[PDB]
Image (tube, coloured by chain):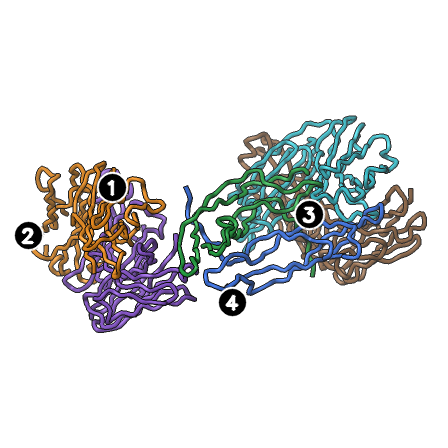
Chain colours: A blue, B purple, C orange, D green, E cyan, F brown
């Protein structure tokens, strides 16, 4: 027997972001990345008022080091690479 | 279920005027008729009025047609009740409610006290355990919330960490024109949290043999 | 308006009983009726609507019936937590109109109170008033008589009692009575409270 | 600037599920729902070993009541409606 | 950075045999050559051997060609070192490392002790403050970890809630054939956490005056 | 193999100094060399690789150079937290080969130890043994002489000392010395420190 639904409020929530090919190299997508994905903070959730989307008031940029593993034809190469993560830190319902 | 929370009530001199607001979680508010219902202390429920979906129409109980205006804000999801030329008759808890014929959603209500008597916060005294109270494996203790006006006064024990063993008596109106209330708790042989919104009094009184 | 006439105004009923509350309208209503339960202090909870429809989460025992002018709430197997005040509401025509209400008490075996007495706080006698409190714990039925006595003297007038609503399981009442005195008068004189109740062979007293 | 990247582990994480039209009524979906979305638990995250996807070991079904608000070509109608939520409670890295 | 954790070390009788494993967070392990490097107590670093990307090839330091086999599990991301006919020469910390010419990622290492001597856990005695330790506006206390074998013994204070004021001395090998170590802390005028993996001893010893 | 010859074997250097460590190979290496720093107890940390490339997160002051046979680590402005042992590693040909290492001590103003003494635990004398401990706290340089005699003359042989590695900021040493006795011998009947930072030998004792 059912119970009463609670709205997902507009706040920052831990999400999983996958680190794609295009973020380091479009021209040659014949390589890999470690780790393959990282945690981030994003705004998500619904708004109580009509015609207000949940959106971020404050975004933090956070650069992070990963490894690019190029299959250089037959042989692995390990390069370091930095990627910049966009973290949301606060949310507001806005028009 | 759906939330509603009334505010705007308190103490008001006779002949005075007052606005009540009732706020609703959620945009659902914009899609429903909304009624107000009142109820005087120790008396029956009395419909006050309603307002239609889009604001299209307003409807009132005859006893009230002159004095009250229902107004609605579809953005804030707030319902409003404008009250003028108030008298002792109007001392009541006023409810917000979701009108669909049959009122399936209620606020908790807001107490309007119509009176030309001074606001005053309570003094909190301890009812301390002894021979008298320790009686048997269990003992009785409490606090006396004295000489306040108007109602209401909420009481918690150790901020809600002691819930079940409580007995909060309705306040009695003293000959003075002020209210006095007792809250007691049973424990095996200890702070009451007193909140008196109208006077912005909040007291945390330790009770000690 | 249409006048709602609920009956009866009040009643006691033992745990388990079947109970019927009746609502009668001045015109034909066509099931534009609903039933509310309302605990002491609290907002009304909708039980039946459209005459006979139960609301989600309303126990099976609550039952709506009626047609035309005459309508009925039936509580089939009365539970101690059913103590409340019940209302009907017409909504066939504006204005909406309710009944005057039915105050339901649960009725049970006699139980006598436990009696405790509280001296006034020294911290309160600093303010120069003395308030003495007598506590009757978990009894039935409601009717009791507290009487204050300082030395041999029945104190007449300066006592005030308040009584809890019925317990949700235990269906007992609890009562507090407050004798108020000037600090001076208090310091003048033993203090006692003498309880009279059907569940007592003869009057119990508590004093210091 | 930089600092060292941490893998998103395979575990249950709070997500926001929107309650769609198709879940109560496809037939000309001319109506609304409250609340419009609810929190859920889902598995997400990457796996340390090669060729292991992150997947749920234990899913809990959780029915919840909402309201359906039908614009009845003019006038709102408020019906109650239940929807069943699929919550993940544990995850494991499992083979392809 | 990338993680590596060696295990498989401990105490081993001479002539005996032993397998070390070194585990790596992450599938990156499958895409790199991997080396082992050793280092005897109070001596220099010595390459042990390496293994190629796909397993294609193995490579060893001559001193070791007879005795050691490097093996690799590309599923578990584990590197393995098989060691036979061990002697005192082999008592060392053994490192796992990421071979790309230049070893940019290291395990912490695993201590192999080659000896035909009895494992034994420590007795923990208090070095208590008084007069001579209260010295300045500052006092000296500690615990003595005595008669253990083999190395190593880790020490924490109040489970890591006291970190900075610590001084953990290297153990001295007694004439007995057992190790004894002292850890001391400075505090203004208190439990050491002793962990001795090889004997599955863990002690929490309070020190007081 | 190719033999790596690091120099010098060991050295002291004052805070701020420029320091050079040199590594020489038996064959021409072509920058297939790297430099490691390694603190006491811990794994090696890669500093320079490919002869001259700094690793991400390695301070600016560490500097790689060399060609052919001869290679150099240069620490430009020596910091107290640079105390370590440094190694070079060839990787032009298998087998990989390292240098014998350079143990770097930070050198600083003389500082004399604070001396504390510990009786044996009664709880330890319950077992067969009495162990007495003398503590020298935060001194420089390393060289000190502890000598035992407790309600007694000179105990010769039954003492053992251990010494911390240098402090990461303060660059001092700390030392513990343990005289061991039978419970009996203990019940039958001081530690005397000699150090350049002392006018004359300090003693600490209980009786």
Query: Marks 1/4: CA distance?
Result: 50 Å
Is E134 situated above or below B199?
A: above
Q: Which chain contains the residue that carries disc 1? A: C
Residue assigned mark 3: F164
Q: Position of residue F53 (x, y in %)?
A: 82, 57
Q: Secondary structure at mark 3?
A: loop
Percent coordinates x, y for residue E24 in the rendering: 71, 42
Q: Which residue is depicted at the point 16% across and 60% down?
A: B174
* Mark drawn on residue C75: 1
Q: How far apart are the alpha carbons under marks 4 and 2?
A: 71 Å
How many residues crowd around disc 2 within 10 Å: few (fewer than 14), some, or many (20 or more)? few
The reply to whether residue F28 is in sight is yes
Within-10-Å neighbours for mark 1: few <14, some 14–19, many 20+: many
For the residues labelled 2 and 1, the Cα–Cα distance comes to: 46 Å
In the rendered image, is residue B209 in sight? Answer: no
- Judging from the image, what secondary structure is the residue with disc 1 in? strand
Residue C154's tag is 2
Q: Check the picture and name the quadrant holding the C terminus of chain F.
A: top right
Looking at the rendered structure, the secondary structure element under dot 2 is strand
State the CA–CA distance, disc 1 to disc 3.
83 Å
State which mark lies toward you, 4 or 3: 4
Q: Is residue E92 above or below residue A8?
A: above
Q: Nearer the viewer, mark 4 or mark 2?
A: 4
Mark closer to the chain start, 2 or 1: 1
Q: Chain of mark 2?
A: C
Nearer the observer, disc 1 or disc 3? Answer: 1
Which residue was labeled with disc 4? A95
């Amino acid at each position: 027997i059912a119970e009463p639904a609670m709205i997902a409020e507009c706040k920052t929530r831990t999400e999983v972001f996958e680190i794609s090919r295009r973020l380091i190299d479009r021209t040659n997508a014949n390589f890999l990345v470690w780790p393959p994905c990282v945690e981030v903070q994003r705004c998500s959730g619904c708004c109580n008022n009509r015609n207000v989307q949940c959106r971020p008031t404050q975004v933090q940029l956070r650069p992070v080091q990963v490894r690019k593993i190029e299959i250089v034809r037959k042989k692995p190469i390990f390069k370091k690479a930095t990627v910049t993560l966009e973290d949301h830190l606060a949310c507001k319902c806005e028009t | 279920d759906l939330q509603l929370v009334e505010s705007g009530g308190g103490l008001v001199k006779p002949g005075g005027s007052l606005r009540l607001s009732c706020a609703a979680d959620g945009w659902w508010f914009g899609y429903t008729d909304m009624s107000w219902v009142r109820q005087a202390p120790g008396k029956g429920l009395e419909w006050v009025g309603s307002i239609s979906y889009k604001g299209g129409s307003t409807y009132y109980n005859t006893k009230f047609i002159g004095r009250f205006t229902i107004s609605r804000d579809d953005d804030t999801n707030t319902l409003y009740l404008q009250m003028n030329s108030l008298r002792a008759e109007d001392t009541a808890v006023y409810y917000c409610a979701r009108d669909d014929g049959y009122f399936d959603t209620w606020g908790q209500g807001t107490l309007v006290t119509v009176s030309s008597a001074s606001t005053k916060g309570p003094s909190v005294f301890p009812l301390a355990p002894s021979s008298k109270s320790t009686s048997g494996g269990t003992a009785a203790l409490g606090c006396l919330v004295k000489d306040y006006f108007p109602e209401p006064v909420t009481v918690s024990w150790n901020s809600g960490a002691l819930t079940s063993g409580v007995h909060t008596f309705p306040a009695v109106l003293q000959s003075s024109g002020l209210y006095s209330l007792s809250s007691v708790v049973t424990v095996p042989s200890y702070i009451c949290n007193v909140n008196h919104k109208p006077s912005n009094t909040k007291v945390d009184k330790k009770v000690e043999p | 308006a249409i006048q709602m006439t609920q009956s009866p105004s009040s009643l006691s009923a033992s745990v388990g009983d079947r109970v019927t509350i009746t609502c009668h309208g001045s015109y034909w209503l066509s099931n534009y009726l609903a039933w509310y339960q309302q605990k002491p202090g609290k907002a009304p909870k909708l039980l039946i609507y459209d005459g006979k429809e139960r609301e989600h989460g309303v126990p099976s025992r609550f039952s709506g019936s009626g047609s035309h002018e005459d309508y009925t709430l039936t509580i089939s197997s009365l539970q101690p937590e059913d103590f409340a005040t019940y209302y009907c509401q017409q909504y066939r025509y504006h204005p909406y109109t309710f009944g005057q209400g039915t105050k339901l008490e649960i009725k049970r075996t006699v139980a006598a109170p436990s009696v405790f007495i509280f001296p006034p706080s020294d911290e309160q006698l600093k303010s120069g008033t003395a308030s003495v409190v007598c506590l009757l714990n978990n009894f039935y039925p409601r009717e009791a008589k507290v009487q204050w006595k300082v030395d041999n003297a029945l104190q007449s007038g300066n006592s005030q009692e308040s009584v809890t609503e019925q317990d949700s399981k235990d269906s007992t009442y609890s009562l507090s009575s407050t004798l108020t005195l000037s600090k001076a008068d208090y310091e003048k004189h033993v203090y006692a409270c003498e309880v009279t109740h059907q569940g007592l062979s003869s009057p119990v007293t508590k004093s210091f």
